[PDB]
């Protein structure tokens, strides 16, 4: 899809505004709105000058402005704006060299895919994530200097009309798994795409979910553990690799899974805590990664066991042979999370890392001399951030991740880890006020 | 003080009830009230049969009842009870062998002092702690399945009458440091005693503080960090060792401190995380042990620096030469905390452990190649508990701490660590609800 | 009705979503919504992969996913959904063998009918149930750790428009018995069908009743005893057997009832407590099965007496000769309840079990030596579950009921029986608080 069709869309729909959208390192979606008459054919080869004071690494204290370069293939009319608006996802570029910014998640995902095609291991990667959310009727939260409080108060029309709006915005939905045990938790299934296209689709997914919940007087949250004792929100990711139109993950070994797939799983397992720094970036994210029942915390693979973090779905077709990693949560930044998973898999393929043996029939039942032995995902955000700081190397292959970008990301996550670490919590008043 | 004087006190004061008090492993103070006519001369050589279903290690699923053996030298009239009551602190003994229970904090402190006298290093140990508390006008807290909340709402008569009641109950008070910056925080200074006598005095201290605050319609808390950003409650402990009436901590080295004292500091520094498991037993306790200004988190000693955890007070008398460790908090169990500190010091003296060099002029200012190098106290309760589980050895010298007692203590602390770990906190709703 | 007509219905009505519905062992109706463009001709020969974490036996801890295979003959447009939805009832199949799941109520009902046709006793079975419900204006209930509470606050338009919506959804209604004594209690009469078709119709019946009551701001409940002293909700079931188009229940014996019918009644009477485990599955269900007036608790048959649980309606046509069993309640799972009744009748026919003699003129008036003699239905849910555990055999004939399915059902019922058993009830506070 080119720019000429975008101008044709502008004239066709009588678009008044164009909303240029990009993503922080935090994953939040930033936008600049320009009038539709400011969009010309030349606008797609210079972009728009932008002031980079966005939170995170973009708050670099030496530098000048950045460039918003739109991707014309991502244009879609916004369903929620009263004045007809055309949404375009943009990359952040350095104004001089006109190259992708080092601290741009979308540019990093594009670099990861380019490095994939460069190494010759595969031609493309297919990602299907399963982001789950919570729908609540109401919620009030706050934390002043004299205390804290939170209070959450828990239809088919909302779910169906979410699916309708998602299909308006170019997503191909194919199910909707409302859950009656742990009521409130929903998940819409969508079709697989490549890495950066699927990350853009996740951003659209969250946008639609939030706004449709708003219009029905509800509140949706993609927060990994919004509520005590009830099951948390996860985002399982199915990965496949394709070269010239055939799976590299289809083979003859365990559960019909190929040798390259086994090294992919080995690479994911080895770096899973550095990955956890990016796939599980919040402190809330580790209140659902606690050892127990149905918790994706054991770093091993099994088609049968459902305590293993890496699952191998059984499909009656060799053309659909993928691996599902289950520890990521929907609070991740899709670009950074997906790039981290891809690079871990590529480092596993490159170094012939063997995962080991399938943990078919060994759940959290605490085997006498195996519960401690099996690798686990990070236990807290500090541990994941420290392991990322130590294990930068697999992210730096091919120049996808800069040391400066990783440093800025880690500092930005730490300034929230510390705010959580130093406030006193009401459960500690319940337990330790008298003590 | 003997039992005959206790019976004389019963007849003299017209005592109606006798309140036998002991301490959990959690540090909470348990009691059994018996009528004064049940107290005879024989009562002081059989004790009282007790059902040991108290929380913690005392909930042992094989065993029968325990024996409450009173210490007649700890008898004191209760100021707060309408019907004249005589308080007596008791030890928990095994009914058959009639020996101190292995999971009894008071028995463990007595064993630690007996091991001190046995090793011949010193004859007695003097402990002076400085427990600080917060006085609030009101507080409401809670945590249901649909949220959490806490709300704290912040005179000379209360402080003075606390000191009066403490001197009624045998404590020798000598100051009262109300603090105007960080209003609400108080601390009463008292005179030094030996380990187990000082721990009993800390229990009396907390009892008096809580009840006097109750009667004035206030709420006192010995909780290490009850309130955000304001300075937390600590319990600095001054240790001295005496043999035949002279300090072993008085010498000619740094700040007039002796060689035995230097090995004591070395032993405290080496085991400071296993100690932290006992001196800093709550998860709240590590919201005040965060690196920063005036935080006793650097494991080093200095008479001048006040970022070092171990201070060496300057006193114009060789007869008062002590070391102050500043990381313990008032939520500790005085018996277990003091026994842990004493045993760490004794292991340092026994193994000639040298602390190193004084960190006189190096605060938290982050030296280029020293902030990471210097040992730190544990960063979380899980880390402290794991280090205790790994570093049992110094606690087991002389049989003071049993493996079974340590295991029960660690499990009892973990069941609260986990409850804190798995609830979602309102600050995480502030930070991650939209994310 | 085939799949081609279902695709034609999709195109004709402009259906946007397809709602695939199945039933728990608890009887609750579960659903998965897929977009209408995901429904193709091939979709009706592979089904949809489903995650079987549904409550009950489906929570089996070894197994992988299940298959939702739709029944194209059950397709009906949903009247209550804003976005046009097509409802299809589905069976749960094992993905490999592609056979009916052992713990699937609908598959069990299909197996029961297949076993009926296999044994050669009859060709088809006609079931007509009479489910009664309560319409309330409002209700609030709850049970916390500090108490419990319930409060129920009690037109022709609602009843008529229920009948209209039921006839929209393929049901053939033929009456509506609002009751003025015991106001609030309603019942819609519908036409007889075969077992599994009638069970599907009961599910539609409950769905329509609940949602139509919702839209008028009411609350309908199929709960056997929602209110004290007033008459409870039952579900009388008329059974008939047909072979080559003629009743096997039409004959010349008592009330024009045939010999095969008499053995059917004998088989129902013999196993009536194992049946009660399935037809009366709640603890509430035995607050209406209490001996007294108009209570269907005496295990005997009579055309005249209305204290007998099994009635023989008098019809002026040999083509309508059926037996009515009156103990089942609308909280039953229609598939399991109907399969249990059919298998009890078939075991009675197979073993030539004679019911005995009609109890024409013997009500609950307590005959001197007959009130104790006559068999009774189970007195509590525990007794019914124990009798089911002991009397599995008649359910296992022909492989309809698996031991594993029965075990899972019993455990799932017990986990609710125990929750009811261990909470204290407000009537026990009225009676025993002072005592
Ligand atoms: Ni168009
Ligand atoms: Ni999944
Ligand atoms: Ni005296
Ligand atoms: Ni001090
Ligand atoms: Ni039609
Ligand atoms: Ni009837």
Image: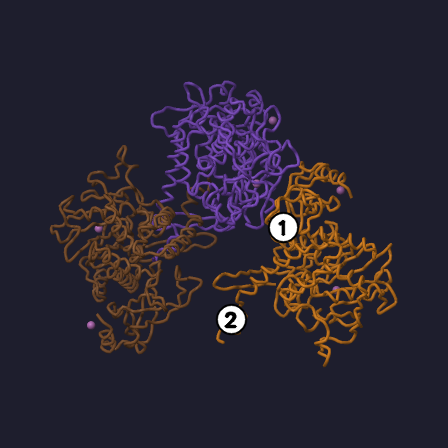
Chain colours: A purple, B brown, C orange
x, y percentage for residue B110? 27, 61
Q: Nearer the viewer, residue A43 or A426?
A: A426
User: Which type of secondary structure does the marked residue at label 2 adopt?
Assistant: helix
Which quarter of the frame holds ligand 5? top right
User: Disc 1 beta carbon < 8 A from ligand 2?
Assistant: no
Q: Which residue is mark 1?
A: C58
Q: In the image, is residue C405 above or below residue A174?
A: below
Taking the image as drawn, is residue B230 in sight? yes
> Quick check: C21 left or right of B202?
right
Closer to the chain start, of discs 2 and 1, is: 1
Residue displayed at 73% across by 36% down = C41
> Quick check: B67 left or right of C353?
left
Q: Calculate the distance from the C-alpha at mark 2 to the C-alpha at mark 1.
A: 38 Å
> Quick check: A68 left or right of A357?
left
Q: Which residue is mark 2?
A: C429
Q: Nearer the viewer, residue A213 or A185?
A: A185
Q: Nearer the viewer, residue C311 or C211?
A: C311
x, y percentage for residue B321? 16, 51
Outermost right residue: C252
In which quadrant of the rendered image does the N terminus of chain B lie? bottom left
Please state which of the two labelled residues, at mark 2 or mark 1, is closer to the viewer. Answer: 1
Residue displayed at 64% across by 64% down = C386
x, y percentage for residue B303? 18, 44
Residue displayed at 29% across by 67% down = B89
Read off the chain for label 1: C
């Amino acid at each position: 899809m080119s720019a000429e069709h975008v101008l044709t869309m502008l004239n066709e729909h009588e678009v008044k505004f164009v909303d240029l959208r990009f993503t922080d390192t935090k994953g939040k979606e930033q936008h600049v709105t320009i009038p539709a008459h400011q969009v010309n054919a030349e606008f797609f080869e210079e972009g728009k000058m932008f002031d980079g004071s966005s939170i995170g690494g973009w708050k670099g204290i030496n530098e000048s402005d950045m460039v918003l370069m739109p991707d014309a293939s991502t244009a879609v009319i916004d369903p929620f704006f009263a004045d007809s608006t055309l949404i375009i996802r943009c990359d952040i570029l350095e104004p001089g060299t006109l190259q992708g910014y080092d601290r741009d998640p979308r540019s990093i995902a594009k670099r990861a895919e380019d490095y994939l095609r460069s190494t010759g291991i595969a031609d493309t990667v297919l990602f299907g994530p399963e982001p789950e959310f919570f729908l609540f009727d109401d919620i009030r939260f706050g934390s002043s200097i004299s205390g804290s409080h939170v209070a959450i108060d828990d239809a088919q029309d909302i779910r169906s009309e979410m699916c309708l709006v998602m299909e308006q915005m170019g997503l191909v939905v194919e199910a909707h798994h409302h859950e009656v045990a742990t009521a409130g938790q929903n998940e819409v299934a969508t079709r697989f795409n490549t890495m950066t296209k699927k990350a853009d689709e996740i951003q659209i997914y969250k946008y639609v979910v939030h706004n449709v919940a708003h219009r029905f007087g509800k509140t949706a949250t993609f927060m990994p553990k919004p509520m005590f004792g009830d099951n948390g929100s996860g985002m399982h990711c199915h990965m496949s690799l394709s070269k010239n139109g055939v799976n590299l993950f289809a083979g003859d070994k365990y559960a019909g899974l190929s040798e390259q797939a086994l090294y992919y799983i080995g690479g994911v397992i080895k770096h899973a805590k550095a990955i956890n720094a990016l796939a599980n970036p919040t402190t809330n994210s580790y209140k659902r990664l606690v050892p127990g029942y149905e918790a994706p915390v054991m770093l091993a693979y099994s088609a049968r066991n459902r305590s293993a973090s890496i699952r191998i779905p059984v499909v009656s077709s060799p053309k659909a042979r993928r691996i599902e990693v289950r520890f990521p949560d929907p609070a991740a930044n899709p670009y950074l999370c997906f790039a981290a998973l891809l690079m871990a898999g590529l480092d596993g393929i490159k170094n012939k890392i063997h995962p080991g043996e399938a943990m078919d029939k060994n759940l959290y039942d605490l085997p006498p001399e195996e519960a401690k032995e099996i690798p686990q995902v990070a236990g807290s955000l500090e541990e994941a951030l420290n392991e990322l700081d130590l294990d930068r190397e697999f992210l730096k292959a091919g120049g996808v991740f800069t040391d400066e970008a990783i440093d800025a990301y880690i500092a930005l996550r730490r300034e929230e880890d510390d705010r959580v670490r130093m406030t006193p919590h009401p459960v500690e008043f319940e337990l330790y006020y008298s003590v």
